[PDB]
Structures are given as structure tokens and as C-alpha cells.
Amino acid sequence: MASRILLNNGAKMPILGLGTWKSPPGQVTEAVKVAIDVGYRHIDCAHVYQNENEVGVAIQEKLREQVVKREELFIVSKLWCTYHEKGLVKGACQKTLSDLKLDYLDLYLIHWPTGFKPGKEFFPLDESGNVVPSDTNILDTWAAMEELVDEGLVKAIGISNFNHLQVEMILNKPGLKYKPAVNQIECHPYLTQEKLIQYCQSKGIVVTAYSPLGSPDRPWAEDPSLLEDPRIKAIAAKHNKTTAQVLIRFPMQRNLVVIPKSVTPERIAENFKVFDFELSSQDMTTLLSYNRNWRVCAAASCTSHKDYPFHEEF
Ligand SMILES: NC(=O)c1ccc[n+]([C@@H]2O[C@H](COP(=O)([O-])OP(=O)(O)OC[C@H]3O[C@@H](n4cnc5c(N)ncnc54)[C@H](OP(=O)(O)O)[C@@H]3O)[C@@H](O)[C@H]2O)c1
Image (cartoon, rainbow, N blue to C red):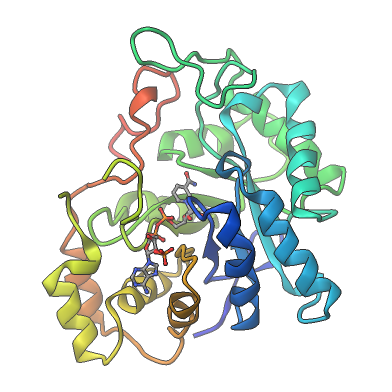
């Protein structure tokens, strides 16, 4: 299968990228350098991960050394929740650009539909354990995202962790100028997302699957473990691949983009070797059968936010 998917802005997005959430700053520079050396062209970043400077060191070095050209890279970042205000969006994008040592992003996402009170703290909370919201609504944040396209800071804009009515609220927005190119959502065999994926794809919005391996290094982890699931290990054995490779190929065959995270050189290389085998239709349906509606990222402290995404069915 092809290495890239056509977005609704006319650009092509590599269907396999390197995730960087939790990648330690002292390891993520090597991780991104290795990834580019072994063929990754898509890096998934975020200001809230606090490691974009070190990601940027790697990108800049590989550009300087002519390992890759900028036009060949697809760099993604995300606007954090405390910058949903109209007057903060541009500065937030420019800080990310500065840290990444780039003059444009290929894709910039609203990281969550939930706006938080602006300030130094990424998660301002009150005594109920609930986040302090901002009164910005998502349509105004979307228009500020649209301005970044028209200023040349980003080639495409999108959303992340939006449920289907929130996607629809953008798509229905009066005076909408740019449709979201992408909705990045958690997706894996324990959270298969059939309904939201079919909705987005029917609209020409590409879906990116995050936490494809079930985020075994997530801070709040004995819960389900995709990588140790004997049923998935059995499918991997049948194909003479690793469990991780099956878990990465799975979304690819649903016409999703997928962004496994690793800081381990051997795994970074191994995770990219997924274009040389095919899961059968029966394999695909079997993997889908494992859905348990289990989320790595439930945003536990935001469940009373008016824009909390995970109340609605999808
Ligand atoms: N939009 C959002 O709100 C959001 C939320 C979550 C994630 N994301 C993005 O999605 C990316 C991926 O999700 P994630 O970081 O949650 O988790 P993940 O990619 O599902 O899993 C990462 C974990 O799997 C390990 N691993 C990687 N390859 C492996 C292999 N071949 N064999 C065994 N273990 C392997 C990694 O270990 P090592 O690193 O030690 O090798 C790490 O502990 C994130 O990094 C981020 O870029 C976005």
C-alpha cells in the first residue's frame, strides 16, 4: 500500500509517523534522528509534551545534513487547551515553530475541544479536581486556526479528540473557510471507533490513530495490555511479524494514519517495517472484535467541561 494519504487541502500525509508524547527530552533527539534515517517522514509533536525543542534539534540536523528535504517531511503539532483564546493562537503556533526550528507546520491541530483558562499552568484546576475552563467556543478557536493557514504558518489545520457532533459543529460553522483536514483520536483494537471513523471519512476528514500500541508507558497505568494480548500475538506469529507491527498495520488497512511512539532505536526501525505484509479481512474483523471501549486518554479532569468529548456515543 501507498505511503501517503491525500488530504482535503491537496497535500499528502505519510500514513506512518513517529509519536513523541512521553519521549524524554534527553532521548527524543536521537529518536527522531533514527526515525528519519530509517524512513519516517512524519513526526507527531505537541507543545504540552515539553520536548519540541529537542525534536527540532533532530529535524534541523537532518535538514542541514541533507538527509531529507523539508518538503519531504510532514511535521504535526497541536494547540494546547490554555491557548484557545483568539489572541493567543498565533503566538502558541509561533512558539512551537520556534522550538521545532521550522518556518511552517504541515498540520496544526486543536489538541482538545476543551479550552482552559490561560496562564502558566497547562491544567489549571479547582478544588473539585475539575479544570478551570475558558469561555472561548470552538468555532472562534477554529477561525483563529484558519488565520494561521492564511498567514502561511501552517499548511493544514485539524482537530483532535473531537466527537462527531463537535466535528459536525465545525463542519456546520457559519462562514467556515477550511474544513478540518484531520481528526486525531485514540484508536486501537480495544477502542476501535467504527462510528466516528466512518463519519469523518465520509466527510473527507482523514483520521489519525493515536496510542496504537495501547500506550504501555502512559503515566496512569494491571489494565488491558494490547502488546501482551495472546490473541494478537497469535495473529503476529501467523504473519511472522511482531505484535507491535500487527498493531501498526491494523489502522493502516482502515485507511488511517498511525503514530506509534518509541525512543528505542531497534523498535523505531522495526515499527516502520509494516509495508511488506497484509492482514487478511478476517484478521481485520477479528482485531475489531476486541473492542472494549477502553481509553488510554479519557481526560479525567475535564469530564464537567461543557466541551468534554467523551460523553456522546461517538
Ligand atoms: N492527540 C492526543 O491527545 C494524543 C494522545 C495520546 C497520544 N498522542 C500521540 O500518539 C503517540 C502514540 O501514542 P502513545 O505515546 O500514547 O503510545 P503508543 O505509541 O501506543 O505506545 C508507546 C509505548 O510502546 C512502546 N513500544 C513502541 N514500540 C514498541 C515495540 N515494537 N515493541 C514493544 N513496545 C513498543 C514504547 O516504548 P519505548 O518508547 O520505550 O521504546 C512506549 O512505551 C504519542 O506519542 C503522541 O504523539 C496524541
